[PDB]
Image (spheres, helix red, strand yellow):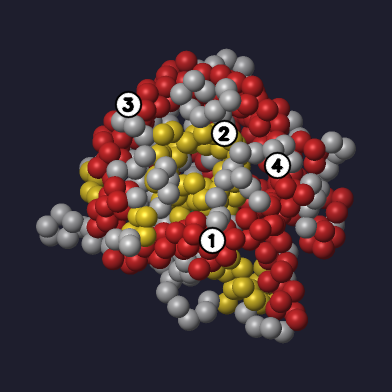
Amino acid sequence: EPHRFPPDFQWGVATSSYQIEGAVEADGRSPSIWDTFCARPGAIADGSTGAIANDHYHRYREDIAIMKQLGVNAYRFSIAWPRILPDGRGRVNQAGVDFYERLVDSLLEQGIEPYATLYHWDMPQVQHDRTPWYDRGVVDAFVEYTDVITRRLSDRVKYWMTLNEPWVISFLGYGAGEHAPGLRDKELYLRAAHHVLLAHGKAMPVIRANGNAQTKAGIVLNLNWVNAASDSPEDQAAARRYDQFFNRWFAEPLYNGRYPEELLEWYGRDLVPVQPGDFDIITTPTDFLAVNYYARTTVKAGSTDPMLQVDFVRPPGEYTAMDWEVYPQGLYNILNWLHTDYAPPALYVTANGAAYDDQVSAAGEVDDPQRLAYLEGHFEAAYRAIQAGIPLKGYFVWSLMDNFEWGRGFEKRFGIVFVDYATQQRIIKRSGKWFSQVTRANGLP
Ligand SMILES: OC[C@H]1O[C@@H](O[C@H]2[C@H](O)[C@@H](O)[C@H](O)O[C@@H]2CO)[C@H](O)[C@@H](O)[C@@H]1O
Ligand SMILES: OC[C@H]1O[C@@H](O)[C@H](O)[C@@H](O)[C@@H]1O
């Protein structure tokens, strides 16, 4: 008896616009906050930018043919607000819309279901200058964008994700200074976090009004499995605080209409700009919850991170090139926690994958057995979740192909397809050849 997934299970790959598209000045696109941030010395580890990336804006048809080789029946991508409303608001850039029309039409004629992310971190610079995420006026700016693009594409796109990873947008963007726009302030991070939630919740009815009864939408949360380094009460408390910060800060508002109270107290409750009616907007019912999962994080009491008073421990085990612990049990644990605590009617894993050092062999192949082992372990965790009655409906590997990995630049490769950046050649890795059999078998051998 092989381990077969449900018959209509969605097997996909995931990307985002700035990480793959390139053509950053093409067809009316304006600079995003990432075009700006890549100029800052020290922001990108290898000094690179996303100006060219995978040149997917031009090569999308070739990428779709790769997806047909991989056997996926779903593709998760993002739309670039700077291509749709290059002035942030106001005049629709027809040529920008036209790209995503051509992309979606090409996917649907290959039988690949489109899963469109509205915001994956590439706000137009001209809009950020008016409404950073810490300014409540960002919410209506994002809803106007949502309205424009959902009006055009909703005849063909059924599955919509509002914002990709609120924790990253707010904390790395405004609290740690690691992502665009590169600010580092507790209050700015907490305002941004709140406004991300409100933007989600006000976009939900717009998506639903522009669609039909088949339309499904939800948010994407990054979640990792958190573990205490010891059982000293101070390490237990530090793990709990980290789990509240990373995993519960957005989930508790979305389902229960509250922040994690003891962390809210620790920060200073008045720093969160909550207005009456906000939790009623944030809790607007969704069709699914999407999860991006990578690792187990082990926390002790310490002062490495001064904001939370925690340090990290690396348990003995296997690690990726990103020094992220490989812990597939954690995926099962996360899905099971969400199911039991929040009961979302459907779950998707919208990103899971690994970066390992890849090399093209003399024969032109890319042999990545560690990445293959990573994926096999996490697909097994997913299968166990389904057998336990968790309504997991789909799984998207991060990523289709090697791409710009934000503050790591091009030096970290997450694809199941290798990209030679000198030539734009795509080579399916060994992991991608294995995945090609998983999607077709609808399960593990
Ligand atoms: O987990 C702590 C670690 O997070 C890093 O950000 C990751 C994040 O872990 C993951 O869940 C999300 O999906 O992607 C982001 C961006 O790579 C972060 O870069 C580290 O500073 C931080 O210590
Ligand atoms: O950090 C690895 C990947 O994590 C995902 O969840 C993000 O949404 C991607 O943009 C990123 O490349």
Amino acid type at circle 1 is Ala
Q: Nearer the viewer, mark 4 or mark 3?
A: 3
User: Mark on residue 109?
Assistant: 3
Q: Is residue 76 left or right of residue 337?
A: left
Instruction: Say which residue label 2 marks.
Output: 216
Q: Is the residue marked by circle 1 packed among few (<14), some (14-19), or many (20+) residues within 10 Å?
A: few
Residues at marks 4 and 2 touching, judged by CB atoms closer than 8 Å: no
Is the residue at mark 2 in contact range of ligand 2, meaning its CB lies under 8 Å from it?
Answer: no
Secondary structure at numbered mark 2: strand
Instruction: Say which residue label 4 marks.
Output: 197
Front residue of this view, candidates 442 and 91: 442
Q: Nearer the viewer, mark 1 or mark 4?
A: 1
Q: Is the residue marked by circle 3 packed among few (<14), some (14-19), or many (20+) residues within 10 Å?
A: few
Spatial distance from mark 1 to mark 4, Cα to Cα?
A: 30 Å
Q: Is the residue marked by circle 4 packed among few (<14), some (14-19), or many (20+) residues within 10 Å?
A: many
Estimate the x, y position of residue 37 in percent, counting from the top left: 54, 44
